[PDB]
Image (cartoon, rainbow over all chains, first blue to last red; front, side, top):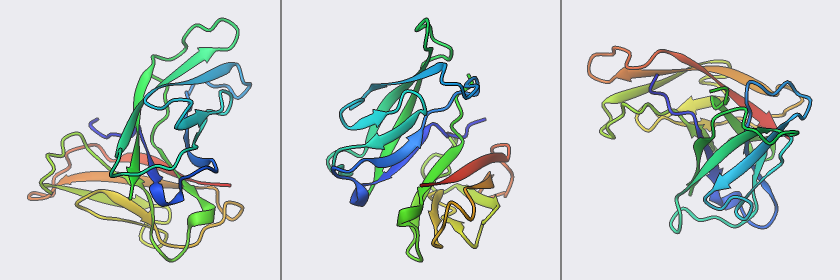
Length: 99
Length: 99
């Protein structure tokens, strides 16, 4: 189908210093036992957006502004903890900033 | 792939009678001219969540509590604005309340 789901939305009003929950990465192969390691890559990964590599939760940790930068293209990876070998194909997703 | 993307995340803290931007329905068939009509149905549609049928923008319009309900199962439609014929299969998506 042509539906676009691989995006998250962030209200800039609510961003700033304190981590603002954005969304979470999740593979249907995650059995729930933490054997998947979620990795963020691409625009502002680790700097503008953090990820918990176990839960896949994503937080914005900078003050954001739509006029400055209206969106970020990131990449999601899902690796086997032990091996570091990919369990999903790496997938781009976007975080859009709403004003 | 197994990446689960058909979900939006609503922080409980920011909900209220003021519309809280939740996310957006979007078809890649959308030319940008309003010839697509986005329709939203299912759990909390119309009472908790509304949609702009042109932009596809979803807002939560009630104050929500995770412990009362952690998630809503909704349905997305994309109709050709002139004929009312579907341009996409009707697709399920989820809105998760967090905190």
